[PDB]
Length: 110
Image (cartoon, rainbow, N blue to C red; front, side, top):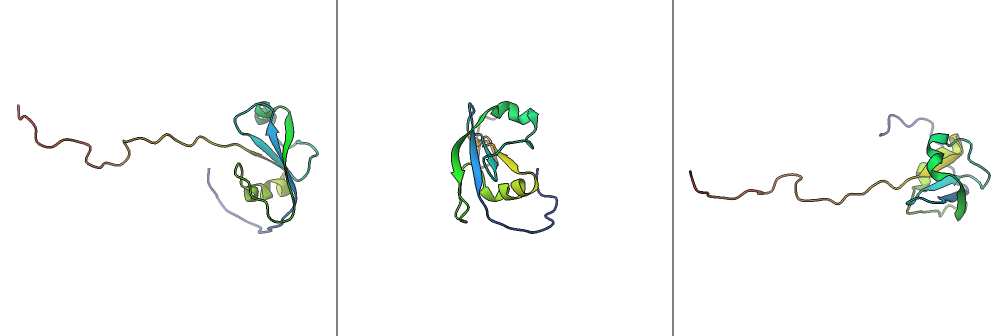
């Protein structure tokens, strides 16, 4: 999942609505207004179900969120009209990547 090509370039600010999943980890839907979601696939909405109004994004230009990137939604409401944000799994990290002296020195030659 990356970027094959940009294309037309039209950056325009506006107002958006951030909905919250009735019961989920941290899923939120985005739309140019609180009207409805008809572009979302019934396969994904199955997890959302009945969205609710938990946060409204104003249209003054200063709109920054920590869940989804308002900029990644701009091309979603202008082309489709809706954008669902889903926080992916971070990671617990560990001690195995790369290789920094992970063995011992000198041993008992058998």
